[PDB]
Amino acid sequence: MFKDGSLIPYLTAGDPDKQSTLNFLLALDEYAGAIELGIPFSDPIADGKTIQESHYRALKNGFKLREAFWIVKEFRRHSSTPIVLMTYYNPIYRAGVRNFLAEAKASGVNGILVVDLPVFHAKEFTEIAREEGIKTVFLAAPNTPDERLKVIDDMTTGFVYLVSLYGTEEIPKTAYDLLRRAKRICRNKVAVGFGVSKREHVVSLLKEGANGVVVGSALVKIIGEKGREATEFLKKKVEELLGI
Image (cartoon, rainbow, N blue to C red; front, side, top):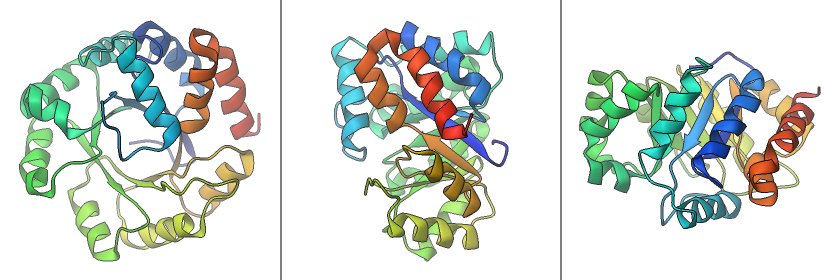
């Protein structure tokens, strides 16, 4: 869904408020190949500490599901940068899969990633996303075996998202191994979320085959640190990571 060598910002919707999220997106668009907008959930057990706290902040400050669409809709007035909505299944399941996907599409969302999509529902889910015109983004971690990478690649219409809960401040070998295994199996492009925080992390991951590098934690840390005034500091971090 994005150009090779793309940096992909990840932000939690409504952290600290939907208006600020929109501001952050507009300020980082010029550096983004695509953007991941995360829907906050009460139990983000698949996320790292930093991003879990951004979920807590957003909910505490009163974030509401459809405010995420507001953000995408307003963003679309100024940009056509691909947007992937990242969420836990619970919200979608409760609101109605097709209803949510249709509403997502209508707002400008291009793809969707369901962090904990029950394998039991994967089939029907992908079929519904296809019908609603939304591309799919599936996740895989270091403990994902080659056989499953293949199944994941065959269902993916957007791009494969490789993650690493490991942390760092070096990228773990187990994370590089996941990438190395994925590029050998995936026909889809792949993005990596290995918690980069330094220029060398980006240069290296791109050199090792990542079509796109996502930047979430580095940005979110600054947001829970500077609140609405995070913007300018975010631009500098993304610039640092881009060697500019």
